[PDB]
Amino acid sequence: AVGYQLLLRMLSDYSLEPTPQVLSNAQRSYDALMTDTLVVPSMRRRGDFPVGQGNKYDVFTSDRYYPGDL
Amino acid sequence: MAETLEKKHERIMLRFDRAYSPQKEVREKCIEATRFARVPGGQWEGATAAG
């Protein structure tokens, strides 16, 4: 991926137009690289959202509402 | 004749076990129903801590 990106950014020095196969290889490698380091954030409760009676917020927890902000 | 008091006690314990063994899963349902009907947090019991 690094090599293909460098080649794409450097070919202009020698005034050479890249061929479609090199472009396809570069974009495929870049897609793999971005796939490797992908993280999907997870949303959290608002903070004033109630916590139901089923959670036993008397003795099991003190939370009447979610903190949900951090 | 079971003259000694100690001999009379393990018989009572065995009788208690014999009486407790059969009627074990019915009283469980009875207690669960009472708890589900009256205890404020008893309708979600069994999954109280889940996330």
Image (cartoon, coloured by chain):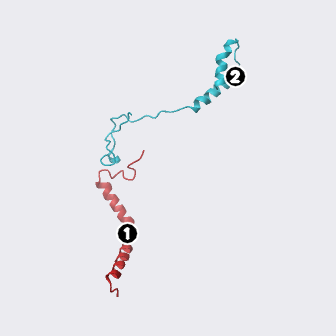
Which amino acid type is shown beneath numbered disc 1?
Gln
Which amino acid type is shown beneath numbered disc 2?
Val
Query: Foreground: B50 or A37?
Result: A37
Q: Quadrant of residue A18?
A: top right
Element on which disc 1 rests: helix
Q: Chain of mark 1?
A: B
Res B23 label: 1
Mark closer to the observer (2, 1): 2
Relative to residue B28, is residue B40 depicted above or below? above
Few, some or many residues within 10 Å of mark 1 (<14, 14–19, 20+):
few
Res A52 label: none
Which residue is the site of mark 2? A22
Query: Foreground: B6 or A28?
Result: B6
Pinpoint residue B4: horizontal percent, then vertical percent. 33, 84
Element on which disc 2 rests: helix
Q: Say whether mark 1 and mark 2 are on the same chain.
A: no
Pinpoint residue B7: horizontal percent, then vertical percent. 35, 82
Relative to residue A55, is residue A47 depicted above or below? above
Pinpoint residue A15: horizontal percent, then vertical percent. 70, 11
A14 sits left or right of A54 in the view: right
Chain coloured cyan in the rendered structure: A
Q: Chain of mark 2?
A: A
